[PDB]
Length: 130
Image (tube, rainbow, N blue to C red):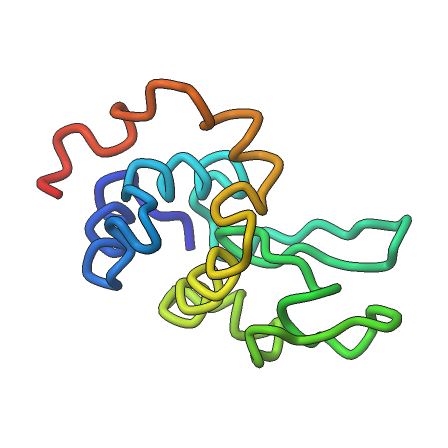
C-alpha cells in the first residue's frame, strides 16, 4: 500500500516514533518519503552485494532481516524480510527502531543524509495533527 502523507504521519506517531531516540516524526517522514515514496511493497535489489532493501524504510537484508538468499547476512531485527512488505507497518517500525539504536542513529540511511539532514523537513508533518 502507498500511504497518504498525513495518514502515515499519524500511523508513525501511534507507533511511538515521535522523538524515538531523539528523532522527530518529520525526520521519519522525510526518510520514508525518499526511501519508498511511502510504499510498503518497495524493493531494491543490490546486484553488487546480493542484498535487497525492503519496504517503506527500505531496510537491508545484509544486516536487518532474513531472506535466506543474501550471502553471509545476519538478521538483527529477527524478522523474515517478508514482515517488511506488509500493509501494516508495525513490524517495519520495530525494525527501524532497532536500526537507530545503533551508533549512527538516523544516519544509517544515506538517503536521510542526502535529502533530510540539515534541511527544512517541517513540510512533511504540516497539517497532519501530530
